[PDB]
Length: 51
RNA sequence: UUUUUUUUUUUUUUUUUUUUUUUUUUUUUUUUUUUUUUUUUUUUUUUUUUUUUUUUUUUUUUUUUUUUUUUUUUUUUUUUUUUUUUUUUUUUUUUUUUU
Picture 1 (tube, chains in turn green, purple):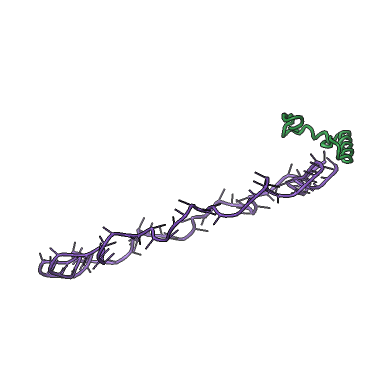
Picture 2 (tube, protein in one colour):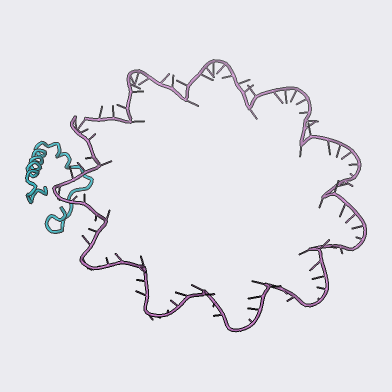
């Protein structure tokens, strides 16, 4: 993601912090991530399939 | 609780390649890192050949005694108060396992 636009990016996530793995317990987050993975596995020719 | 490649974006798979090339060979000559000449023990003055000797000697022996670097006497676990004898023990427990 450092080459997202042209070249410049700064990382906002701490390499040792663990404040985001709680989101795996959320059912809706798992449902949307499974939705996007299932939909973009069917269409691998899309530009946005990098997600 | 759930899990169980400290696997995975999709692609790919020589830490291969401009093209041309291939002795980290070559000016031509040459080919003892041989040579003035003449020599050839890094031998020799002539003598000489124990880095032997004054003579005398020849235990780096000895005063005479002596001869456990033994001994007051008594003794002989560098044992012992009595009691004891896992440098065991509250009870409960017994993966320094587990959402």
